Image (tube, rainbow over all chains, first blue to last red; front, side, top):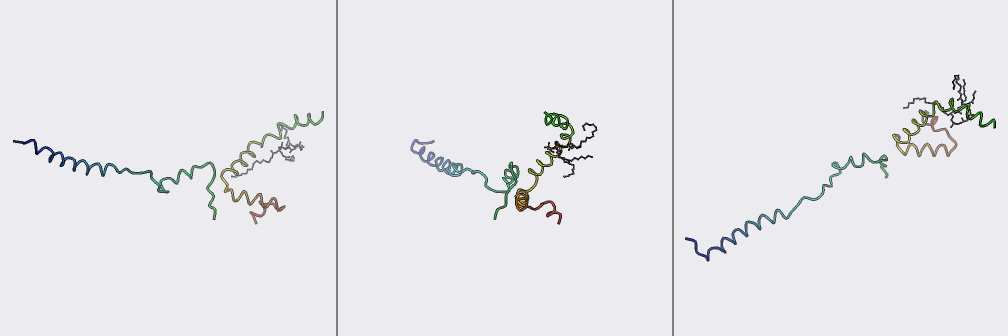
Amino acid sequence: DVPIEKIPEHANVLLKKIDACLEILSKDIGEVTDAEAHEMYFETSKFQILHIY
Amino acid sequence: SLAKVWMYASWIPRGIPKAMANELSSAAAALAHPEAIARVAQLESQGKNPYRVARA
């Protein structure tokens, strides 16, 4: 009950699905840059912080 | 010589506070803000006693 001409339609459907998946999964989260997350990297320096203005 | 005798005689007296003195000096160099230390060096370059200045 499934002719062989109907296969590439199914393949196209699944290609659309997996492409919709990979366009999201291709994205990734980079390194965090919030200073509040890294303030203790500077708090723990071997010298006190110079607020120079 | 007599200088060596005085050295070996005054070694033990002279060295009793050296630990606490070096401790306070180093703790000052570490904990104190470097701007204060620079001001101290400046005032000592100006012939002033920065401790009296700070107290005043």
